[PDB]
Image (cartoon, coloured by chain):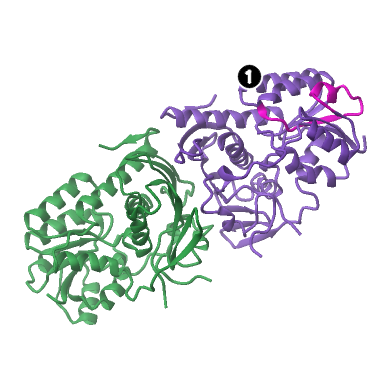
Chain colours: A green, B purple
Amino acid sequence: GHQLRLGVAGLGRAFTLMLPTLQQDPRIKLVAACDPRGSARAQFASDFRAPVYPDIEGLASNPDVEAIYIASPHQFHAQQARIAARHGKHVLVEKPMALSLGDCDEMIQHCRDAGVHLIVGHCHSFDTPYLSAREIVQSGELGPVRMVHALNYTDFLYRPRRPEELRGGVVFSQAAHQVDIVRLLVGTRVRRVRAITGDWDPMRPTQGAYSALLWFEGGAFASISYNGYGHFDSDEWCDWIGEMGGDKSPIWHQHFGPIVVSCERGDIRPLPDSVCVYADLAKERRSLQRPVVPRFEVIDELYHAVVNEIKPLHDGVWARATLEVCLALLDSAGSGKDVELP
Amino acid sequence: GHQLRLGVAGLGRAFTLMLPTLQQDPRIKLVAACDPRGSARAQFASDFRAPVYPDIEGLASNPDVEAIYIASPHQFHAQQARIAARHGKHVLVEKPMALSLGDCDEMIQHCRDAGVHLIVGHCHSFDTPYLSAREIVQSGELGPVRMVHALNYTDFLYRPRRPEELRGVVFSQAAHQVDIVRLLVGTRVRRVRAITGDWDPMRPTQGAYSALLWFEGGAFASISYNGYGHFDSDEWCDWIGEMGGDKSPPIWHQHFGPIVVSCERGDIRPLPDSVCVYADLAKERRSLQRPVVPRFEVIDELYHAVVNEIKPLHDGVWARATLEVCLALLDSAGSGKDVELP
């Protein structure tokens, strides 16, 4: 009702990254969890004094639950969503939505049939610096976007796996964030993608880096780069604030690396603690407000979806489009060809 | 001999940018100039008490001249080189060498026939931070290069034209960038794919681009450039300018924007005042020595070419290869297709 009664499916990393949000936002009440391993069930039931269950069917059958946060691994998203929706519970799914586009269509459809909302999980595109810059672009103040430059040098490939674990892989975890932000900011449709991947650690044999070109409806283009072999660290170019808002010399907004938005009449630079605008007149650090609850913008989007029926932006149709770009990206780097999108 | 007796053809901007170098390097003696405009002839003859001439044929006919610095506009490079070489004078040509590849072949040939050196002019790839990082790559210390990321946000499109200027980001700006990536990666460019932007109707040229570059051996590079002068990337080079000046109230090395070199075992970041190395063990700011003479590395390359017969790196064969990439770049952005390079 006033307080949103929320179930959590899958008590892993995604969940522990989200947990400070769920604890601190007074709109949220955590009522019920499920997870296959009892060690974790015993752990949630302890801390929250709340019914835990082996599976989704247990969690969705509880009538106190209003919505479920699906934080399990992706091969399980489509199945878990279908179930939640069957039992009429709204769905916030961590990224990526799913593995395949068919999976996504099924998800969007099952959620329509139940008349419940489908919002895709935490995504860096929810972060308010980017939300703020989207507003500048919409306001027309600087004309349309013509070019976007995005890069991010992380150590994602060599982060110790956490106890809660449960099993996100540069293109499916990291590229989704990036693509998502560029889509948010430009605000038109991706028409063509061309990408190169790098894979140069034999010990750790995955695609740990890429560079890509992205073509947009209306003539803007974007260049996106990512490296996760953890040498150079691009936070240095974001006022030394971390992905989760901490200081790296009272925390700040979440962000996902240096991004420069080139519009007709100026450049926009989103920071965790401001938005820099470079224009024909002057150059400005436009102030932002310290977030009182981390990732509150995810909860706003859910809370206004459920309580006030306001269409959420990061919906299933949206999340799906990102997946498409990520698939196209991976396909382009795999063949040696451009990929055109419908 | 001991002191290199140098002629200058074309007393424009290229020349005035080079002038502090030529005055201050004790190896260099300025003996003679030519230029079509008397106002400039009168000006050089005054300051340097030296014979000036209407054209190249005047300058090259003077037997005191050992070598000529060709700083005229490019449509004049090939004809001027042929002339200097006919009269057996070595040739330092400002960038771009020429506008055509046929022009370049003629130039390389005319200089071979005369048995004189052909070095291409000031190019940012001569700058010692980049030279120093090339050495790290050669030393094998970090394995081969796997990825290069290069960007540069300038105001090149809206720089007042200077008095001297004998009055365009691909042949001036992209050459610098391509050149550095070629220096650092150290193999051959095999494929290029590029997008240009052109979004100011007042100033209708290609003022920005992003490109992918494929290399022999599997490294890839991403290069971005924007010259509509809003954001200023010097912010990401310790606030030092292109010509080594400080831009945040004794100068430093020349440079051409943020560059990150990704090798197998670590990242290399050339700065105007150091080279940062990020490796598996630690991360280091490796110190460099202040330049006592700006662009001394250009003079080293010339002086050791003429006096001691040491093969120069930025030779005619080399400069030419860059042009190829620049042509490929422009071609790719013009059609919508990859360009493969012999």
Is residue A130 one of those drawn in magenta? Answer: no
Return the x and y of residue A2 as percentages of the image width and height: 14, 76
Of residues B215 and A311, the one drawn nearer to the viewer in this rendering: A311
Instruction: Name the residue rendered at 63%, 61% in the picture.
Output: B284
Which residue does the numbered mark 1 point to in the structure image? B102
Magenta residue span: B53-74
Residue drawn at (27%, 77%) of the image: A23
Quadrant of the image containing the N terminus of chain A? bottom left
Label 1 packing within 10 angstroms: few (<14), some (14-19), many (20+): few
Left/right placement of residue B320 relative to residue A3 reads right
- Taking depth in this image into account, of B248 and B35 the one nearest to the observer is B35
Residue A138 x %, y %: 32, 54
Q: Is residue B213 left or right of residue A148?
A: right
Chain bearing mark 1: B
Total marks drawn?
1
* Rendered residue at 16%/59% (across/down): A80
Question: Which image quarter: residue B237?
Answer: bottom right
Residue A150 appearing in the image: no
Q: What percent of the width, then of the height, locates residue A270?
A: 42, 60
> What amino acid type is highlighted by mark number 1?
Gly
Relative height, residue B68 to residue A305 (above, below) = above
Residue A42 appears in the figure: yes
Question: Front-most of B23 and A158?
Answer: B23
In the rendered image, the vertical position of residue B326 relative to residue B147, given as above or below: above
SS at badge 1: helix
Left or right placement of residue B227 versus residue A224 in this view: right
Residue plotted at (89% across, 30% down):
B51
**The C terminus of chain A: image quadrant:** top left
Residue B73, percent from left and from top: 68, 30
Furthest residue toward front: B39
Residue B59 is one of the magenta-drawn residues: yes
